[PDB]
Image (tube, rainbow, N blue to C red; front, side, top):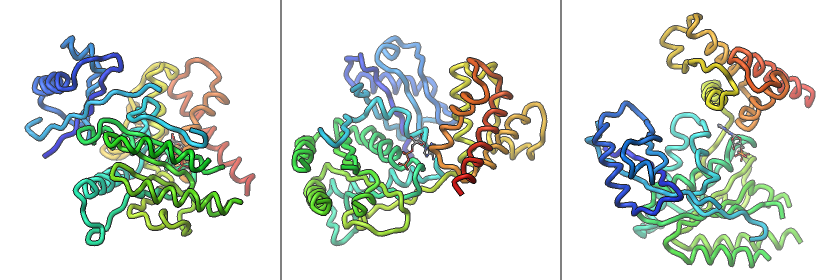
Length: 364
Ligand SMILES: Nc1ncnc2c1ncn2[C@@H]1O[C@H](COP(=O)(O)OP(=O)(O)O)[C@@H](O)[C@H]1O
């Protein structure tokens, strides 16, 4: 069995990754027994304190332990460009809460695609290509998940590629000049190059006819390369569109979150405010599973978690975008103070949610 361990090497570190590889594996033999996903940020060994920010075990270490040691990179006309792994995308993957194994299977699909591409599997005999489509209603994290997926793959494939690239083309819009810069990045075969075309449905809605055909033909060229992956998103979940998108061999529906997911999302927001001490004092909050084990009995330990559970349920229907914005509105409208008890914040969050749906009915 294989266990994955992501090692965040400090930007200021100059040590070889083989040295870090041996240090981290000594640390794991020390602790050796693991209960689940655990992350060390403080170390006793001074070589690790110097060169490693965090060691995270991610989903008894007699399994096969795979280390992924990476450094974050701290820093083209109509395109955004990041060198991967990018500091901007650090923590994005974990901030996206989907139902079980949406992100897992998506990672595995692209992993198999890259494996098949790397071994020159004949696609006439086994179906695969280099295009990925996430489709969903707007605000479900599709663009973020593409970026987070590109970051995960670069980190997980650090043995085959030395770094990654992400080019985000802004659909709202020389075309030869942009794809020349993309080809220069592809020319470096030590790099896994991701090209992200957001909301491709706007292309078929948009003189405008020539620009589209120019981009589709440029896409057809770069996808001929082994180190290229094309990520696309569509905010219309149902409709058919453009060839390379409709023929994408990986299609994933991304819908709005369930009440179970909303609960986790809110929990992550409340944890963050407690970490920053905007919510003070800190209090213990229960997960759904923990609530289910006590049959949802209302007592001092559970009262506030039950209240959050009920806020999550009347939040059903809202997108993730709105959900992670509501704690900001809750604080700005109903707290307006540097500090607030969790009781006060949950009440504020509840009002903010009601306000969202009042605004909704006015649009109806
Ligand atoms: N399922 C989710 N869980 C947590 N946060 C989410 C989720 N979906 C969206 N968000 C938040 O909304 C932000 C913007 O979403 P975005 O990726 O632009 O949506 P889309 O591209 O699908 O329109 C994300 O960066 C994220 O913080």
